[PDB]
Amino acid sequence: GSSGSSGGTVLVSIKSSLPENNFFDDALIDELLQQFASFGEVILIRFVEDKMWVTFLEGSSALNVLSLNGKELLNRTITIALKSPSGPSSG
């Protein structure tokens, strides 16, 4: 539950067993792209130390893709989550 955000960066993680598997491969990504297309047309993708961020054309689009929150793909449970603002919105 968060409204207001100038951007469109969403966090995406995959549930695995080994610590050297948390890394996203060509399949996990390639496949994801399409899945995200169903709602928003991905434009930029940023890989985090352990997490995986994904940018979208607009912020709203990143709100629709949330429908993939938890969706399991390639025998790998994916968990999507918006990037909550650490600091207050007002100024």
Image (spheres, rainbow, N blue to C red):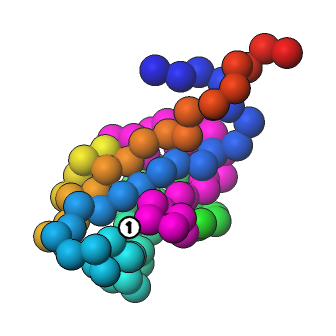
Residue found farthest to the bottom: 26
- Between 13 and 3, which is closer to the camera in this rendering? 13
Residue 77's spot in the image, x, y percent? Answer: 21, 59
Residue 10's spot in the image, x, y percent? Answer: 52, 48
Query: What's the residue at 28%, 74% (across, down)?
Result: 19
User: Looking at the image, can residue 2 be seen?
Assistant: yes
Q: Which residue is mark 1?
A: 32
Residue found farthest to the front: 19
Residue found farthest to the top: 90
- Between 13 and 17, which is closer to the camera in this rendering? 17
* Highlighted magenta segment, given as a residue range: 47-68
Name the element at disc 1: helix
Question: In the visual, does 91 lie left or right of 24?
Answer: right
Q: Is residue 32 above or below residue 38?
A: below
Task: Residue 72: name its quadrant.
Answer: bottom left
Q: Quadrant of the C terminus?
A: top right
Query: What's the residue at 21%, 68% (across, down)?
Result: 16
User: Looking at the image, can residue 28 be seen?
Assistant: no
Residue 59's spot in the image, x, y percent? Answer: 63, 40
Query: What's the residue at 59%, 66% (across, down)?
Result: 46
- Which amino acid, by three-letter code, is at mark 1? Leu
Query: What's the residue at 23%, 61% (across, down)?
Result: 15
Residue 20's spot in the image, x, y percent? Answer: 31, 80
Q: In the rendered structure, does residue 59 fall within the stretch colored magenta?
A: yes
